Image: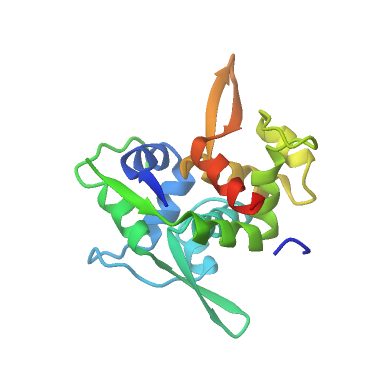
Length: 101
Length: 93
């Protein structure tokens, strides 16, 4: 293509994500059973979520743009990992009620 | 009280460099430079990408606080948030 600081309320972000089935699952996909932040590609993320690939891929790409996950290029592939911001958003889900994940 | 200090310059660069995110955010700025309200269907018709891609992007932009949502009857109408406005401002100068 040709077209190549703020105080954020992450509690309110957690609330909105909590109410979006795909967003919630994409974010928590990066947390393992031990509760640690793991590295994944989009294919991996999509494999643990029962929604279309285009939907999941776009959500992953959006989360990168938003600064919730960082990107590591390897060959033609991209590996994603939670950022500091992404982890703090995850932490907002501690003792938070969830309705139909 | 949990707030986070966001570097808008970083987000701005990431959004700017991604053809999909840039197009979705900028959809909300009319040809005259004024902010405008749009539903998901209108955003999709403005962009040469699949409907599922565009819809998921709008949804994640809402979650991120880049766009605000108003209910009109049963529909969801979206506008740039104060944060959304600030990101666009990074392109402006």
